[PDB]
Image (tube, rainbow over all chains, first blue to last red):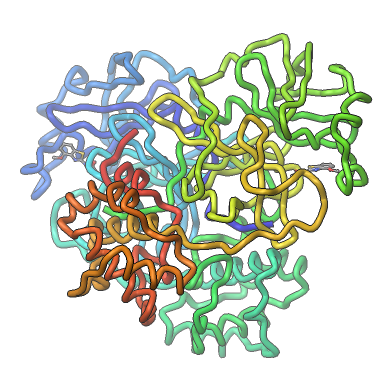
Length: 304
Length: 304
Ligand SMILES: *CC(=O)Nc1nc2c(OC)cccc2s1
Ligand SMILES: *CC(=O)Nc1nc2c(OC)cccc2s1
């Protein structure tokens, strides 16, 4: 029993983090086989960041200007290229600690672990979600860029995020490992406002199932609802519309608890309309939306 | 910017987790040098757990009854002994992945990372605090016993917890790595109720400093207080009494923000008396008490 915001074990990713220095800019890179992946803005000064022309800035850069350091040993850069917003630095040595891995582009509402790194050294790990506005609410200080987000399926790391930007509102933007930004963000120090941070409805419901499973049941009520009726209330409270796809995804949690998805919807509807009245659910005073149904099943069943 | 509940990177501890099987009981062990540490109740059946005599149960056990498996390779047990509530299994092979480590017995209010393991395989990592009632609010399913809690200072793992027990109220009890229980708990399936779960006042204050640092300032007020006046309000709300030691520990956060500790106390006092009025602090609807002052400095300064 007990339900926690839980990150994947970080060991497999710790073994991939390097320091990348171009001129006087140092950030983190991901070393997989004989390639080091890092944000292309490693080539920028703070001046450059106001209006960078990356292709032009890159012409002034050779392999030997990219200093790659793995622990206290230097890697030899034998090639470099820009793919979207990342640089791929070919090194002469395959990372001996390369895990089985994939690059996946996640959808909003999907959760992943971040290994916060500074100077290629891991400082900590935490669980995030890709917000519906394609931001993440991270913990990222200067030097944190190139820190990655990942899921693990048994022994295979799926890398889904690389950290690039803080928005003036203190939320975070970055790319998949093909260097494509999540949402409309760019690696430019410019006016970039996030859209509405909507609540991931299917994740709240998943987490209400986790609560019932772990003994927190005070918010179960006598009501049901329909997707259309629920969705009217979702709209009002800036919750993502719930689809039949979400209902199907919650099927296993429905089965195990014996609470129909639409009944749990009715519980969520009353919680939105009435608030928590000073009560907590799994030690939270608000509705948690950064557990997926898959996360709840995993933690409630003990998958490794 | 951004402030997250952040665990230490788990790699150094992942490399220490083994499976320990005695008869039909399987749980996790910690392999440091040529010793495997595990809960002594690995020798118990569920029947045994109602009233175990461990010294008597142990006489029926030889080295070859303790099956230790590191990944898919078996370790040879060449000795065993009971120290308090842990078994120390001497194996013929030093763990090649042994990190620099210490065993530390933490005080209530101190935070640590847990690497949840099942069958010697890591499933996830999360941040805990030793509660003032010497419980922890973990996520621990069957097979989770022998999972450990730790802090990391640069390259040195300080192990402070090993998981032993779930209380019927769904909270968690365990030992330091000398096998001494935190609080009055025992490795017996008996009536064991936790005392008052008081709030760790110095940790809430630390986290209010983290909020100011990260831009959440709405709860700063025009008032100050004294330790004695604050403590009257703490008593009423089941908050730990604040000492001059706590004030001194908060000194660095005081300095960096320019908010005197006692002024932040006055902010906390108003929050206790008035509630949050439906507002959030660092994305929380309640006062977070599982960040230490040291945790806030570390995350706010980017230590690795
Ligand atoms: C996200 C992150 O760490 N960005 C960084 N940018 C710089 C920089 O830009 C001009 C100079 C020095 C270090 C860093 S880290
Ligand atoms: C905390 C934990 O995982 N305890 C376990 N106890 C047993 C047991 O006790 C009778 C039998 C089989 C497996 C486990 S794990």
